[PDB]
């Protein structure tokens, strides 16, 4: 962030006003406050532009859509590979809703969209946006469609429609900070004025890298930096190419026209094909992915992939290693030994409660590692597990002396029984077998 | 105009050939990251196997067994149907060899391996029962019995290698080298193998992956590190990568548990679990993907036609 003075030293110094400003020094001041871009001055040398533009700054702008509890933030990514350093902001997921639908249908579909939320590893993860599309090609219909949708959800919106449709819908929706779609070569002056008027983020849309960059430069020239990029791929081969280049050029070349997060559409009517294209876009660089499906089974896999890809490997995922009680167990209920990797704990807790089995679960502290990982690492020992049985207090919670091992660690049972003084049962390898084990053997 | 940024990569993934004569399949050879053919070459697409157990599976989900229900007790007929389902390669897993199972011998397994090989027009991958002591005993016998066919033998590990590698060198087979999601472990195992003078183009690295939601992200990054190692000149990393997709995907509760209300339609999510795991690891730079469901294979093959376009 350089002051107008700093950025003026490299200017043409013509004071020709062609950038809209009265003087070079006052043009620089407009850009310093983000009121104009360098592309507004036609005469600035390419050397000076590089010096100024290559000045320190985040390669990809952080863009916010929506406000309050439901705000989406994306951008501020610095790397091409998560092992270089983590991915910072999980991509938004959006579900398309068309305004050719009846008011009733619109509400019922947005209601279903509100339900795409899922427990993964004991945390809730959900779709972030509703993309309302002006397919009716009528301003009044679109505006009533958006108002109607907003009655049934707190999720931020992407508004897809002509400048006329968008202006009508913004009357009500402009205060909810929606993303507008889109400025094109035909409409951009009108779309930018509308964006500034409501202070909302604006998608820039053009075909291929060349046309997208030239369009972004005309728009930043008018002083609008709150931006999402759409290169318009015809298929997932073009999309991967475009996404790779946009991310590479922003980060590796400091190419500022590409210095924003992207939107990507996987709308395919074949759900397997839609889910696979979206998956490619999650893994490679998409800021927002728009889909056509409300089916939980189509969204669950994408939620999960997003979660995984955007996890920071540096963080252990662990639960407090204590006795947990499931469905208010009595002194007679089974005691299941497991580890404190959160994934493992919630898998087991999920199968036990799912089978409606009151029980105790004992997540031994492995530093958040899985059963066989901790075993191979020397972190799930007979000695360790024996200590948990003795000092956790489980001994006072149950009348019996029996505890049940994961089937995959069965080789531990003998030594554990000798150290702990508990009768050790070997359960199934998979927790999915617990229900049947309990029924038959307990 | 925008100047497309083109990496100049020093090197390439070696090209491995499986099978022999009219049965061959080639994979690897990549001088670029997946699909970026503006900066280098992709002489081969990703390749796909479907699994065949020598004796029928006793734990499979109904939705998994159905596509095979007519052939599932006959490993020869089953393998033929895999090929008809579009598999590049057939992966025969010998579960019967298990010491706590039917515990079949080297000689016996050797004959079943020949029968499958003989009935199909594509290369054969052979997977053991997973008990090292037993697998080290049966592979030298199977390899001799199959001598000269160039099968893919799965697999060699840091503490069990020499038997399976010796059979590969003597009898003309290619090997899978398995190490647990670590670059340096995988390299150290490739080194030991090549010290026996098995050629660098006779090896395929197995990262020992997790499926979607189950450690796919660790797998993803190891595989990207493998590709980047190859491309930047690290020759020990220069070999193609196998992922056992189906093996892992179908253990997921999301794939195998037909009633979870929160998770939506079972048929869709069961297949997505395999296809999404596949595509993720294709994006990561994997080469050979060992799958289970023919429908998963069919949709992934379609996705591939689109992304190669
Ligand atoms: C992801 C992964 C990791 C991650 C860590 C993730 C974590 N926090 O643990 C990383 C890459 C760091 C890790 C490292 C290593 N791991 Co690792 N890796 C795995 C991988 C791919 C998935 C582990 C996982 O998340 N499992 C999912 C959880 C949910 O499973 P789980 O805890 O087993 O729980 C299920 C069952 O046990 C059962 N269950 C659990 N509790 C209970 C209780 C009862 C009563 C019952 C009845 C059932 C039950 O049901 C549960 C779910 O439904 C697997 C291979 C694979 N596909 O599984 C290996 C694997 C677990 N790990 C392996 C190894 C050897 C390693 C390393 C030692 C390799 C190395 N670097 O040296 C290390 C050691 C740890 C370390 N960091 O030094 C080995 C273990 C060898 C062994 N089993 O014999 C495996 C099997 C790979 C292999 N070699 O085949 N790896
Ligand atoms: S257009 Fe360029 S030369 Fe003219 S006043 Fe503005 S900054 Fe100065």
Image: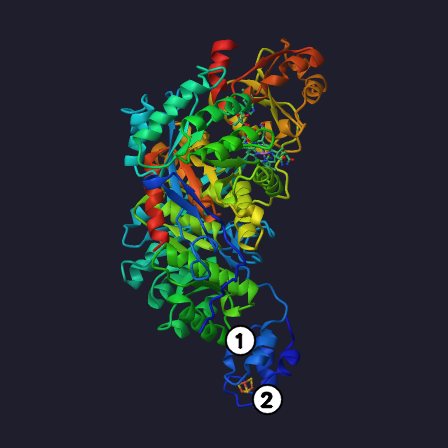
Residue under label 2, please give it. A13
Q: Quadrant of ligand 2?
A: bottom right
Residue situated in front as seen by the camera: B125 or A405: B125
Foreground of the two, A107 or B254: B254
Q: Is residue A139 above or below residue A54?
A: above
Q: What residue is drawn where x is 58% and y is 10%?
A: A332
Estimate how packed mark 1 is, as few (under 14), some (14 to 19) or many (20 or more) residues with alpha carbons within 10 Å: many
Return the chain for callout 2.
A
| Position of residue A390 in the picture relative to residue B307 (left or right) | right
Q: Is residue A103 above or below residue B39?
A: above
> Residue at 32% of width from left, 24% of height from top?
B72
**Placement of A169 over or under B112, stated as above or below:** below
Q: Is label 2 on the same chain as label 1?
A: yes
State which quarter of the image contains the N terminus of chain A: bottom right
Residue topped by disc 1? A37
Nearer-N-terminus badge (2/1): 2
Gap in angstroms between the C-alphas marked 2 and 1:
16 Å
């Amino acid at each position: 962030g350089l002051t107008g003075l700093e950025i003026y030293k490299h200017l043409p110094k013509k004071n020709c006003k062609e950038c809209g400003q009265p003087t070079c020094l006052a043009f620089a001041m407009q850009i310093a406050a983000g009121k104009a871009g360098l592309d507004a001055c036609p005469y600035v040398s390419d050397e000076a532009k590089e010096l100024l533009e290559s000045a320190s700054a985040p390669p990809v702008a952080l863009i916010k859509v929506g406000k309050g509890e439901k705000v989406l933030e994306i951008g501020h990514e610095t790397v091409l590979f998560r092992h270089d350093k983590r991915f910072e902001h999980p991509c938004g997921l959006a579900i398309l809703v068309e305004d050719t639908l009846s008011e009733g249908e619109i509400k019922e579909r947005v209601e279903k969209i509100n339900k795409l939320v899922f427990d993964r590893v004991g945390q809730m993860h959900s779709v972030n946006l509703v993309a309302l599309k002006g397919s009716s090609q009528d301003a009044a219909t679109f505006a009533k469609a958006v108002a109607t949708a907003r009655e049934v959800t707190d999720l931020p919106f992407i508004l897809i429609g002509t400048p006329e449709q968008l202006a009508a819908a913004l009357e009500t929706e402009g205060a909810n900070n929606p993303l507008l779609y889109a400025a094109t070569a035909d409409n951009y002056e009108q779309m930018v004025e509308l964006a500034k008027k409501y202070n909302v983020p604006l998608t820039v849309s053009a075909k291929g890298l060349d046309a997208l960059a030239e369009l972004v430069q005309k728009i930043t020239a008018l002083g609008y930096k709150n931006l999402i990029l759409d290169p318009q791929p015809e298929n997932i081969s073009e999309g991967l190419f475009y996404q790779t280049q946009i991310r590479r050029l922003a980060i590796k070349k400091l190419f500022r026209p590409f210095g924003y997060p992207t939107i990507a559409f996987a709308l395919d009517e074949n759900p397997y094909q839609a889910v696979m294209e979206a998956s490619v876009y999650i893994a490679k660089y998409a800021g927002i992915i728009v889909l056509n499906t409300v089916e939980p089974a189509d969204i669950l896999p994408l939620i999960t992939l997003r979660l995984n890809i955007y996890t920071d490997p540096q963080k252990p995922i662990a639960v407090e290693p204590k006795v947990y009680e499931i469905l208010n167990p009595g002194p007679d209920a089974p005691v299941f030994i497991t580890t404190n990797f959160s994934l493992t704990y919630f898998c087991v807790a999920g199968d036990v409660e799912g089978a409606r089995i009151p029980a105790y679960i004992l997540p031994v502290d492995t530093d958040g590692t899985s059963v066989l990982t901790a075993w191979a690492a020397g972190k799930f020992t007979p000695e360790k597990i024996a200590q948990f049985l003795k000092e956790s207090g489980i001994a006072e919670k149950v009348n019996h002396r029996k505890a049940i091992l994961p089937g995959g660690v069965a080789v531990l049972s003998g030594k554990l029984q000798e150290l702990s003084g508990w009768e050790i049962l070997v359960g199934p390898r998979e927790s999915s077998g617990i229900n049947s084990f309990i029924k038959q053997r307990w | 105009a925008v100047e497309v940024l083109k990496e100049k990569w020093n090197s390439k993934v070696v090209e491995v050939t499986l099978g022999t004569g009219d049965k061959t399949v080639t994979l690897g050879g990549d001088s670029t990251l997946p699909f970026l053919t503006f900066e280098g070459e992709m002489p081969n697409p990703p390749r796909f196997a479907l699994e065949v157990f020598d004796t029928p599976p006793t734990d499979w989900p109904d939705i998994l067994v159905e596509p095979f229900k007519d052939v599932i007790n006959d490993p020869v007929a089953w393998a033929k149907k895999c090929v008809e389902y579009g598999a590049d390669i057939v992966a025969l897993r010998l579960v019967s060899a298990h010491p706590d199972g039917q515990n079949r011998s080297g000689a016996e397994l050797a004959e079943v391996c020949k029968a499958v090989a003989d009935a199909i027009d594509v290369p054969l991958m052979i997977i053991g029962c997973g008990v090292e002591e037993k697998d080290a005993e049966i592979f030298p016998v199977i390899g001799e019995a199959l001598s000269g066919r160039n099968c893919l033998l799965s697999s060699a590990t840091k503490d069990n290698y020499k038997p399976i590698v010796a059979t590969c060198m003597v009898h003309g087979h290619s090997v899978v080298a398995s190490a647990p999601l670590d670059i340096n472990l995988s390299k150290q195992l490739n080194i030991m193998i090549m010290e026996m003078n098995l050629a660098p183009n006779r090896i395929i690295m197995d990262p020992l992956i997790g499926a979607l939601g189950y450690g796919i992200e660790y797998s993803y990054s190891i595989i990207e590190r493998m590709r980047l190692g190859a491309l930047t000149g690290d020759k020990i990393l220069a070999m193609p990568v196998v992922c056992f997709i189906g093996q892992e995907a179908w253990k997921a509760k999301e794939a195998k548990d037909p009633e979870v209300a929160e998770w939506g339609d079972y048929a869709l999510r069961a297949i997505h679990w395999e296809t999404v795991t596949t595509v993720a690891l294709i994006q990561a730079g994997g080469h050979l993907f060992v799958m289970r469901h023919p429908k998963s294979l069919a949709e992934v093959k379609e996705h591939l036609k689109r992304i190669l376009k």
